Amino acid sequence: CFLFICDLIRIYHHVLKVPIHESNMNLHVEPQIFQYELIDYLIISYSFDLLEGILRVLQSHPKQTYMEFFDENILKSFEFVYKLALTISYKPMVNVIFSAVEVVNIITSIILNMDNSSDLKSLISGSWWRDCITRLYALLEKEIKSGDVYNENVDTTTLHMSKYHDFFGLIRNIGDNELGGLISKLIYTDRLQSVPRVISKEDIGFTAPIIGYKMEKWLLKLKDEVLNIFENLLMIYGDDATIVNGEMLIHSSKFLSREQALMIERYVGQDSPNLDLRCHLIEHTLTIIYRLWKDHFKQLREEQIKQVESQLIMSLWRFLVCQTETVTANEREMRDHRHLVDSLHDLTIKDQASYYEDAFEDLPEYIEEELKMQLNKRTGRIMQVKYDEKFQEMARTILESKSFDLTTLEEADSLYISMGL
Amino acid sequence: QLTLTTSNDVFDTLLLKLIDIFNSDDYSLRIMMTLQIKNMAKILKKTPYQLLSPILPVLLRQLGKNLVERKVGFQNLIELLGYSSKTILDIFQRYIIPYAIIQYKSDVLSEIAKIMCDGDTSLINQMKVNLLKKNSRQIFAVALVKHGLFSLDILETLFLNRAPTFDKGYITAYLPDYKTLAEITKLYKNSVTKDASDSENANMILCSLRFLITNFEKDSKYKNINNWTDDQEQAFQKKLQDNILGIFQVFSSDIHDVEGRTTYYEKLRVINGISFLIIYAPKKSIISALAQISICLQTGLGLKEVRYEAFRCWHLLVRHLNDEELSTVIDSLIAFILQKWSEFNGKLRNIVYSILDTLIKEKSDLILKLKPYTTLALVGKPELGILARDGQFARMVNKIRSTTDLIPIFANNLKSSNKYVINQNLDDIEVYLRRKQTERSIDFTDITLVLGALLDTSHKFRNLDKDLCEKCAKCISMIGVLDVTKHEFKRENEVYDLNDSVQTIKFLIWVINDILVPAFWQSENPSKQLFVALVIQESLKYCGLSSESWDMNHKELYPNEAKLWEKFNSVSKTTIYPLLSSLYLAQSWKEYVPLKYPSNNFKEGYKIWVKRFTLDLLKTGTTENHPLHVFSSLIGSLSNFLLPYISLDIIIKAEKGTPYADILNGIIIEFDSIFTCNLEGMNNLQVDSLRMCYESIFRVFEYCKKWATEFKQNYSKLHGTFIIKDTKTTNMLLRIDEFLRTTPSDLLAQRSLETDSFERSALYLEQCYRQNPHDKNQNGQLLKNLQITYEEIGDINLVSKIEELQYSENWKLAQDCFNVLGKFSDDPKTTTRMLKSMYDHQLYSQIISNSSFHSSDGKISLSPDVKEWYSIGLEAANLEGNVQTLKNWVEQIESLRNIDDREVLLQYNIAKALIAISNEDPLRTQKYIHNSFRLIGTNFITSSKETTLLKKQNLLMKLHSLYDLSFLSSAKDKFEYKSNTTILDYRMERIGADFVPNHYILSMRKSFDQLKMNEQADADLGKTFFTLAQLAARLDIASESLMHCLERRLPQAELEFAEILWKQGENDR
């Protein structure tokens, strides 16, 4: 079935590879048809979720028997379909992008969880992970424009999942699945239809931008997937190859600092559902940078530590200007901050205590003493400060690792003096 | 973030401040800037080099002065820029080497040469010398600018400070090179205010201007004015007016820089250039600076981040050529501003406001007397605050609208070339027609010609710009059906030859107005604008006067060239007049590579073969005796025009005595060789290239034919007693004998219809079947082809003896002949014949009755190439059908897997618009109407010169219906809606009165309330069909619709039901 619907997706080359903006000659004069748009897209995403579930049968299958469902045919079919979906040149759709990158993710998960790993890591081609990660870095550098996520936006640098191609998916529900309602008009439901009832790209999609917010909370969790599987690649090789050649510092830290800059410049104050999930996961991508720069410190050479000395040093510096934290160190008004941004997670503490824990009603007095500071450093991690001492010294030791002259010793003082040291 | 907030100019100033906090001699400041810029870059969705190459020229200007020490600064810069040293070195040599040459004599150019040779030491000297040759222009500019001297001794000394290889004194004497004076006028780094240092650098760079080769051997230092003459200025600007054309072709070199590593710093540098020149340049220079200049800075203007500087130079041009002229190029600017004012910020907005108020304070005559659509547009997009800019001009714009029946000017400015100008054209078309519709005023009881202009825009977008196609299409839709009737749908112009003085001069006015402004006002390669210059020195020598001393009326000493340039249409005189002060001549001609090889004619088509072919035929047929000749260097833009346009020299084969008639026969058979190239079983490579060769040679034949016909008509008009008149009858009959001979009719017709055409075949075949047998026996092969070309063009055994009556005023019989022979539902050709027939007289609900879908199975599922039956039927449902009907087919048409079809996809879009307002969401029904409009306006119409709209019936009827389906502007309000019942009674005015589809008294009203059908308005749906059937022999359709309405008990509808029954023929029922 894996390879099967893979060749089916090569059957439906048209929709997965439709011109980025329908360049003049090519026209988006489509019959406004999630009718067959549903047919193609649905097949693709459903089958990609089936690829995820097949990986799962082997993923929880005993790793004494992992030499079988891996073959060059799996890899090559996925080559073609992955490349058809992550269409760097044409206008992809976000269900398929999700699904493909998820397949990449579980693939990597098993690339680790296979015991006799060297043989099958030889089997999967290094250039083939490379053609995964060129498109996956492409993803991470593609962005999220909520206000127009349900509208033809810029050249794929705006993950949209346009209402024109919009349902949930199977191990996950990212859209509104509005077009699931038009599956509640998918067939006549009163007739032996030969061809089915329209689903419509136009009819599908000031009402509930919670739609965009939950879908973006996904795309956020998507980039958690992406960071964690970039991270999983980081583990698949301890001694490594062309996929991580300092590029998993370049692009990884580029995302890490892009998210520092976006969380600061807008997202805190933008103070939305995304905040805490994003900050937890990008501090985690910081930790990815950390373990790369410590253990995988062997690979990184001058050319690429010079291509991105910038990002590296100053992302570490940004996280660093925090530890002393003479502001509150307690729950006085950093809880005001927990209200100005972490208000979403305040709704969550309320909901978990009043709706969503059998025991977290009538608190036993040893837990709110902890809450006052724990949720407070949660919102601090939201608001760029008071990251767990774990996090802060991770960020510090990434930079103050004088074993490599990432910092100039005569100016590390000018660096640190923004905080001390 | 301050940079992020700031726009264009201030943004770039702050980005330079940021690159300063970047090289601020500290790692901390260094790297903080590095992170914030890279984050800024790939969260601006740009690239660091793409955002910094805007300011990197300035940065390397400040850096080149101390590069040797600042290797660390340069390397930090390049690691942040992501690119290497070289790719910015060469892409910005224009502004890094010049400042590099004039620093301390211990220059860093040797080190830059060692940069070009890090893996070798070939010759520092040779890298230096080829580099200086590549940039030999701002180096002189700097040498007289960044240290200010023109005495030859130290002048050459500084040229050879570390560059001795610029030897032999000065290599070829182009100190007044087009490129030299470009790259120095580029240095016009002006600002808003007049600083002492900036003013003095501008004055001393113009001193560098006023030093050129004239004194580069016979030499003060040109750092002041005390060394300039008040007399040499007019010839000086003559030379500089030669200069300017190549100057701004170098401008287009930097702007339209195909390299890609280029950016917009060069574009604002070109802004500076044009500014400087028109500023210190007088009237002649600033008028010869009109043609390609608007294109150079409009390319600047389209770029977001030099829009500000673009309007700066645009405003100083506004100051630099007053109201009586330049009214050509306010269209581009009022268009760009009315078109992007939904973007324009505070600074862009107040500089454009300054544009406008200068326009009002100087050129009210230009705006309101010369281009009235400008006033109407600049008050038809009023949110820009144009009243808030002048206000009391509102009375003037009111005058402009009311005093003028302004349909023709609307057409002409609508006839303009590109998307932005026609974009505002059609926007105000919308507002105008809304005003006319709502105030029952659109003269309809030209508009038709602005209609045709709109559709010609559409077809120039036939595979282009879907969005303005849909705007264009809803504009044809809001203008209406139109079937001549009330007006006249209009479209070999004036007496021409190659013989006599004044008529060849008018042929040349045609030549200039139909080569320069179309394809040379729009040309983008500096080499070919230099060829533009060449051909128009040929032009201005054939109109050789006013090019030496003759003025407008300074002396009035002779009327000859005054009457020349006064017979000359003002666009022509203004577009080519200024060059008259340029005296340029061509070179010794190039090689030959002879002709008459059909092998290269097949493997070449039209890229070079027919063009060298035209080269030879001109250089042997006119030889400087005519303005034909030196166009000899068309080095492929105006191809299918000029290959014929130089194919009239035939007359000199009266008594040839030359190889010219020999090569005339040879060129005719070269065309027949292009014929013999007959698809050879190949692909697109044929179906495009030698196809357009086919239209090329059609135009050449149509061109010789038109020359002959005018040669006849004009010459005989006085009287008819000179029929022979010295061998001219022999020459004309001999040429037409050759034309009666050359006709490979079969291949001719085959490829003629291979191209989307009809008349080429029509006329060629007309003559060569004038040469036919009296009985039609040569017809067997070529009688199966006009009945396949007409089915698109529109000029529309037992089975072969049934359709005798088919459409002969009496359909019913042959019509059900078809519905029978297709009840067999097994022969598709006759099936389409059926549907199209019982379709033409609009039996649309029997068409949806003869549906293979609401049956034992759905219709022909996932309809392959046999979907044309859907094509014929969905419209049948789509106006005679409802929630149930439209839906049951709408979920039976999608069907295919690709979106290939166009007609049934149109009718699909509007079927799903109807089911959309079954769901009743009017706005996204307008969205499906956008999809339908885009579809028809892109994939459903072609150009004029083919098809009067009688056979675009389906198309324009569908268009009128689409507007009525979903358009909200004049009838957008609810108050409007009630009084629009009265205003729908006026839909016939715009559409017409033809029973085909133009009759819209209450027929289209039976659709207004059908689209607006909700509870009380759903009860009014059938009530609005009161005088709908007033039109209804072919009334089976009227029957179905009227049954639907009688389902509401409308007495008028019952009355018209009686009407249809009677019209069948009956009296007393």
Image (cartoon, rainbow, N blue to C red):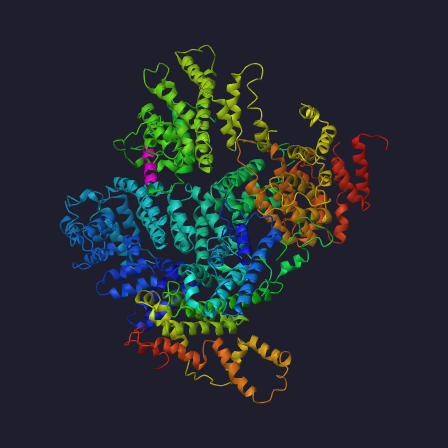
Horizontally, residue B500 falls left or right of residue B949, namely: left
Q: Residue at x 28, y 46 (%)?
A: B179
Horizontally, residue B1008 falls left or right of residue B902, namely: right
Residue B443 appears in view: no
Horizontally, residue B110 falls left or right of residue A399, namely: left
Q: Position of residue B544 (x, y in %)?
A: 32, 29
Query: Relative to the observer, which residue lies in front, B518 or A19?
Result: A19
Q: Quadrant of residue B730?
A: top left
Q: Position of residue B123 (x, y in %)?
A: 17, 52
Task: Note whether A53 is above or below B694 in the view shown.
Answer: below
Q: Which residues are magenta?
A: B527-537
Residue extending farthest to the right is: B1068
Residue A120 appears in view: yes
**Does the magenta run of residues contain B539?**
no
User: Which image quarter holds the N terminus of chain B?
Assistant: bottom left
Count of marks, rendered view: 0
Task: Note whether B862 is above or below B609 in the view shown.
Answer: below
Kindly report the secondary structure that dominates the magenta region of the rendered protein: helix
User: Which image quarter holds the C terminus of chain B?
Assistant: top right
Residue extending farthest to the bottom is: A365
Horizontally, residue A38 falls left or right of residue B359, namely: right
Query: Relative to the observer, which residue lies in front, B580 or A132?
Result: A132
